[PDB]
Length: 50
Length: 50
Image (cartoon, rainbow over all chains, first blue to last red; front, side):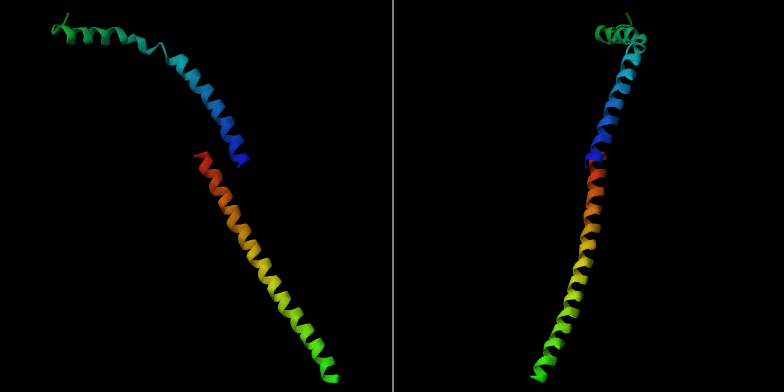
């Protein structure tokens, strides 16, 4: 039980940190589309392409 | 007296043999239990892994 515990705890820690690195490093690249999606949302809310 | 003297050792060897048989059966279902318990151990380990 403790063996199945220490291993899963260690890999959990190392995967949490790796996913943190994924998160911070992929956080801002998708903001290239936030402008155009805001634009299409405005177009939907107005009922015109503007 | 002669017949009681022979019956004593007769019952003695009979008890010896049957007791050896019983302790052999015990040493058998002992490792049976050991098998079952280590199986439960590994299945619990994999459960915690998942």
